[PDB]
Image (cartoon, rainbow over all chains, first blue to last red; front, top):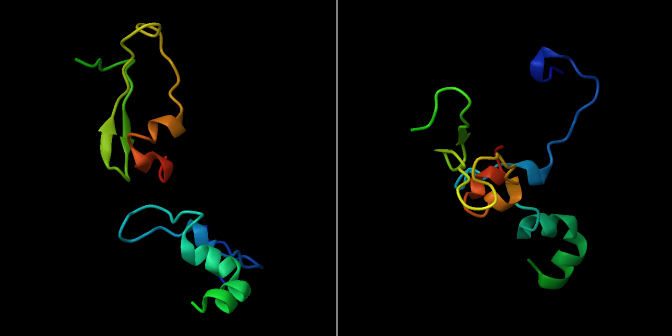
Length: 51
Length: 51
């Protein structure tokens, strides 16, 4: 599979969730946004707060 | 007026404004000083996302 700069890379580099840019703000998402911590603790988070 | 040679000019693409810093009061009046990004980010949050 191709990558940026037209180079074929043998391994995939994941795009970090925290590096995504908000559409309604124009800025990268924070490190303390609730969904990020929810993803980082999904087991306990969904077990406790049922969200 | 700002000079056309030796001047400083900056542009923020998130706050999408052209800004320039000028030193007036003591001590820095005629001597250039370095303005940290984190403290200038207080008056312009966009500098935190896009340099």
